[PDB]
View 1: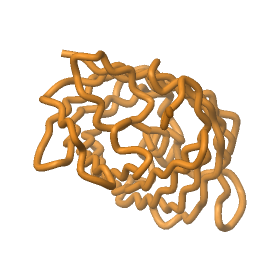
View 2: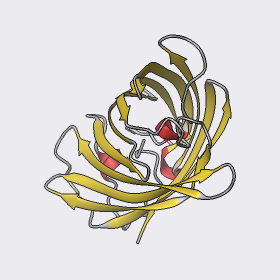
View 3: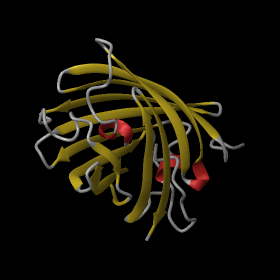
Length: 213
């Protein structure tokens, strides 16, 4: 028996809107859960057609089972399966823009089904997000704390901008296993390395994550 194998697949579906622009994201990927690695290709379709009017970084961060966990730290995310895992996240950008996103992750065979709801609001029309001036998120380290059966993630993110420079964004996330987790972990960290390769409305993503400390 092996609920999560060294190699797994992913299918993504998102219903979203940013500054009133409605859109859907669909994609597929493959990854190595125990190695904290994942790769995927995502397609953005605007409700009114046309190019996506915002930088993909706004939604790129939208799959913890794909985190390399040392045997010293219980793996809450993989333990949540096959029952399922859900998470909720708030984003606070330095120029006033903000967003709320929640996702449900289910498992069937060797494939994870990732479905999300994303609503972004108040982004300045001339800011880097709506002007598509950001490039990638800087690598980061998220603080993970346990609380009454769920996990809390806290990380201050920095968006790399084209002309150089950074744009701050605070992430606050709640991770919820579908069923009661036997072994809860103590407080620790998860370092992330998320990079994108974007060609218009299509984007390829790669993320490497490792839990530690």
